Image 1 (cartoon, rainbow over the protein chains, first blue to last red):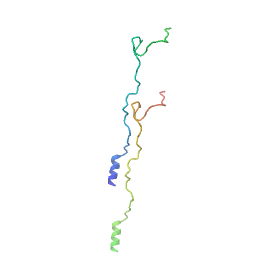
Image 2: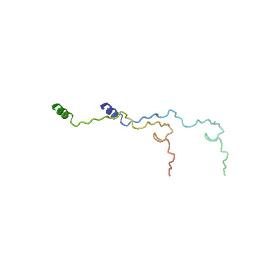
Image 3: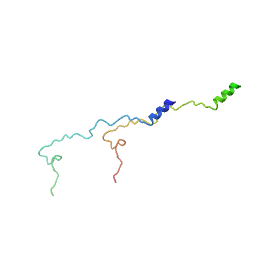
Image 4: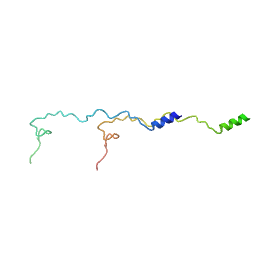
Length: 53
Length: 53
């Protein structure tokens, strides 16, 4: 009885977790797009549909 | 007679208990849920139905 009471007091209400933080860190997708000196900007190749007025 | 009186005096009104504290300590259920770096918090995966206004 004493040992079981001691075990219950020591364990308290501890709940086991099966997993920690997942080791797969990357969530985005790799950027495979080219980048040439003809690009209007580092993020846009052209401004094709743009109308000045 | 003397022996029976001595036994009655020594035992008094002691009542036997068939069981002590049960040795099964855990009462909660194990947390099997994953935890990724995409989670908004350690306890919530997302905030899907939440509206800002």
